[PDB]
Image: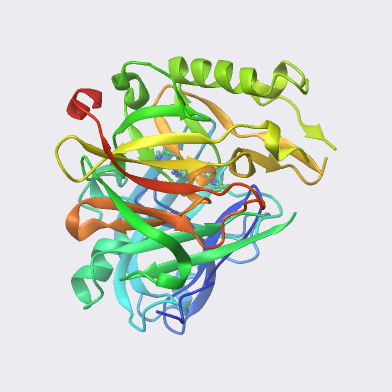
Length: 369
Ligand SMILES: CC(C)(C)CCNC(=O)CCc1cc2cc(-c3ccccc3CCc3ccc(NC(=O)c4ccc(F)cc4)cn3)ccc2nc1N
């Protein structure tokens, strides 16, 4: 899988994208890798923020589906026209598939001014695809039309300073991780939903009812920057993280993500551990991240920014988690693997960690229904 290593690029704060081609002759586009959505959607009209965009009528292999799609999202939206075309990943498996593409004709707060990507590759499942679950997501088409196995793995390497990393399609590459891979079950195939069974700050249990950590869900999402937590958990998390870092004094709004801190005393800040439901009854494992993961440089204001925040739609394990680990989206076996990333940012004293087995009872109770 060595041709796929280092196939991701990006800027800090702006996402990880992969190069793709669409149509005949191929049109090259940079596309955001997003395990928290399920549509392959590309700019297809000259929005001023875009380096380029999909031009359907230049593709001999384009097929119109004569249906529109409108996707609102909190702030803004995207709107487009559905069709299919030939899609490949130059630094991916040497194959080409006919996939659905949503050609974005109108959008607000979708494209980022100064970014170098022109679309989003939604890697989650059909259930959350727009307009509905009959628009086969790209990865489902890939697997179905080729002999590429039903899994992908992501190594996101955090640092506008340049990020990079690897999306290995169809397999795993052992140079990308150290120690062992531990798997948590994908609870249901829509988002990549998981169950968190325990949380620890520098090895001290938060001691909350574990339903609270997954209220109303927990997902693994390469499309989000932050470690996002339900309100009750965020408050307890922050209170304990404040207590650890009581020596040096930061503004009150810092913890709410309203400002930044400069100088780097990594020692002072605690490690954060999530225990995830394991593969066996009463068995869990834990993943641990360092301050290097949750203190993100804000470049264009050594200055840093607090990247844990609250949610009404559940825990999001974003880039804050994923940059610590090699994450294996093992769809064929309905499980997600974590191992220590060969590229995670650490210091000479501590590192990110994946360890087990641990004994955790009543883990099913932690799931929300
Ligand atoms: C509603 C939905 C089905 C389109 C997505 C459901 N998923 C979520 O609500 C989870 C968060 C998420 C929200 C999204 C929102 C949209 C969207 C729809 C209409 C207008 C605007 C948007 C926002 C576009 C967007 C999404 C993610 C990002 N991410 C980053 O820039 C980023 C990612 C990683 C990182 F380390 C740094 C930055 C940037 N722009 C698109 C894809 C999304 N992908 C996601 N994983």
